[PDB]
Image: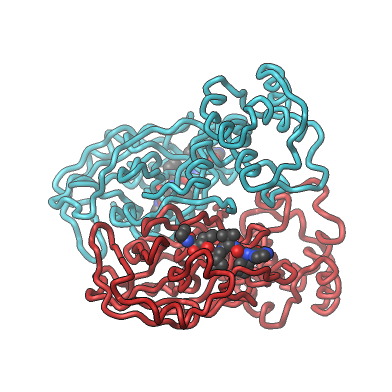
Chain colours: A red, B cyan
Amino acid sequence: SGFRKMAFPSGKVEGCMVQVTCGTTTLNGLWLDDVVYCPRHVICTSEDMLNPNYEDLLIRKSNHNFLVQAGNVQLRVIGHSMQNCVLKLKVDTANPKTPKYKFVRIQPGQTFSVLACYNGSPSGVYQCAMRPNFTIKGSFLNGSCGSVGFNIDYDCVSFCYMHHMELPTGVHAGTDLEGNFYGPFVDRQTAQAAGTDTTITVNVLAWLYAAVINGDRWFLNRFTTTLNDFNLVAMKYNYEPLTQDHVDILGPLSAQTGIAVLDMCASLKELLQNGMNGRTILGSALLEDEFTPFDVVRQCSGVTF
Amino acid sequence: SGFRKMAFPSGKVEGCMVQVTCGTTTLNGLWLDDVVYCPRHVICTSEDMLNPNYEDLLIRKSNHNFLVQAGNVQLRVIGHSMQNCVLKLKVDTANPKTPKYKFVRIQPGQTFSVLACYNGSPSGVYQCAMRPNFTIKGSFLNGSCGSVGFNIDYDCVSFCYMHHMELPTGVHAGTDLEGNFYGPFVDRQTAQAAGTDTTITVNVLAWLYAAVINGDRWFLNRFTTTLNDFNLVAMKYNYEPLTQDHVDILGPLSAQTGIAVLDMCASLKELLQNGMNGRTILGSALLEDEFTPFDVVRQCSGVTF
Ligand SMILES: *[C@](O)(C(=O)NC1CC1)[C@H](CCC)NC(=O)[C@@H]1[C@H]2CCC[C@H]2CN1C(=O)[C@@H](NC(=O)[C@@H](NC(=O)c1cnccn1)C1CCCCC1)C(C)(C)C
Ligand SMILES: *[C@](O)(C(=O)NC1CC1)[C@H](CCC)NC(=O)[C@@H]1[C@H]2CCC[C@H]2CN1C(=O)[C@@H](NC(=O)[C@@H](NC(=O)c1cnccn1)C1CCCCC1)C(C)(C)C
């Protein structure tokens, strides 16, 4: 037993990280087959970033303006193209450590593992959720751009995030591996608001199930609720509305514990309206919202990769 | 910026995990060079575990009683020996994926990454602290025994933990890689108390420094304190005493922020005596104690491996 914020094993992704330099800018790239993917702003100067014309800027570059290094091996770039906000560098060598992979776009509230890297070398791994406002609360320093987020399914690495930038609130924004930003953001150095952040209700319920599975039960009550009345209360506390599809994805945890989804929502309703009165759930004084229902099922049933 | 509970990249360790079967018991082993290490209780029946004579039990076993599998590859065991609480199986093949490694014994309050595995296959990675009472608050299910904890230094994997058992409070106990238990425990199915758990004071201070580095400063005050008077207050709240050597290891964070260690202790003293009054630090309502000073420096300066 026990319940931890657990990341996927990172080995498959480590073998894909490389260093990309253009001009005086060095960041990370992802080397899959014979293509290296990295943020397109590797091509800009400080000055360019206030209002860049990435089309015109990339036209001025040649293949030899890009130095890709995999370890001590300098890779030769044989072609460059732009796909939305990511640059794709064709190299003369396919990565032998390429895994079964796919590019996926995650939805708000889904979780992924981040392999934080600097100079093409991994520094650490952690689990994040895509917030409802399409930011992530990561840990990234200067040089971390091009670090990626991923999930594993059986043997297939699903890449879902590439890191691009930090907001003045300290949160992080980036793209999928097709180069489209999560959220309203554009890669230009201007003020760009993230929306209101809300709490990921379906994940809080998943975590309350995890708590029950681990023997923390004090918050279960005799009350129940309809889904509409639950949402009436939850929206007052800036929680995302719970949908019938969320109720269905919590089905496995409901069946395993014997606690109906709407009975768990009645427990969450009382926690919101009265607090925890100095008590904790799974050691935490705040309600946790960065575990999805599938995360709880994987961790409490022992799925391997 | 940002601050996350970050594990080391796990790739070097993944290539070392194998499955070990003896009788009807299957668990994980660690394959380094031509030796596989695993918990010695792989040799016991249910019935044996109330009072096992591991010497006599191992004498009854032969090399062929042990099935070691690395992927689909069945490894041939050519010799077996016991070192304290771990079994060492000699195999006819050195692991090609063996890294520069060493076995280390960590001290209470130090942190490490756990690669949780089942059937010799990794399921996930997370960061843990060795509690002052020599337990860890892990996430381990049936089949996770033989999973290992490790740190990385440059290119060297320092193995420090092998998982053996779970206590009725839900916490976990195991050995170093020389087979000696952390804490007072013995591998027998009897009631064995863990001592009082205390809060790792030097780590809380490290995390308050991390908060300052990330712009959370509301808890800084004009007060200061001697180290003895701080300890007088901290021991009332079941915090470990802070030593002059702890003060020295916080030196780097003090210098980087310009806040003397005893000034930060004065802030911690006020937090303990008055609470947070509904405020948070780095998003948490409770004081975090599972980041060491070196963990904070590595994460906020970007050390790679
Ligand atoms: C990344 O490219 C990298 O690791 N580079 C290696 C070291 C050489 C780098 C790392 C920072 C975490 N990312 C960036 O430099 C991005 C790029 C892409 C978008 C613009 C530039 C700057 N940048 C940033 O992350 C910055 N953040 C901002 O500029 C915010 N700007 C504002 O909030 C703002 C407010 N008022 C006026 C003007 N700007 C972002 C810009 C994009 C929309 C969200 C808000 C810094 C300051 C470097 C974190
Ligand atoms: C591990 O070997 C494994 O993964 N095996 C694979 C599936 C076949 C296995 C996994 C459990 C997390 N570990 C064990 O089975 C260990 C071994 C080593 C020590 C005894 C046995 C049983 N065991 C446990 O972890 C158990 N825990 C206990 O038996 C506690 N016992 C008591 O608290 C207690 C109280 N009153 C009377 C008698 N015992 C431990 C025993 C050791 C000292 C600390 C407390 C279970 C119940 C399986 C978690």
Q: Is B197 located above or below residue A80 in the figure?
A: above
Q: Nearer the viewer, residue B130 or B294?
A: B294
Quadrant in which residue B228 is drawn: top right
Question: What x and y, as percent, mark residue A24?
Answer: 40, 60
Q: Is residue A301 visible?
A: no
**Side of A282 where B305 appears, left or right:** left
Q: Quadrant of ligand 1?
A: bottom right
Q: Is residue B182 visible?
A: yes
Q: Nearer the viewer, residue A185 or B231?
A: A185
Question: What x and y, as percent, mark residue A93?
Answer: 22, 74
Question: What x and y, as percent, mark residue A3?
Answer: 57, 54
Question: What x and y, as percent, mark residue B132?
Answer: 55, 31
Number of dots carrying numbers: 0
Quadrant in which residue A21 is drawn: bottom left
- For the point 16% across and 50% down, the residue is B94
- For the point 77% across and 60% down, the residue is A220
Q: Is A249 located above or below residue A280 in the figure?
A: below
Quadrant in which residue A257 is drawn: bottom right
- For the point 68% across and 61% down, the residue is A208
- For the point 40% across and 63% down, the residue is A28
Q: Is A248 located above or below residue B43 in the figure?
A: below
Q: Nearer the viewer, residue A29 or A271?
A: A29
**Side of A250 where B305 appears, left or right:** left
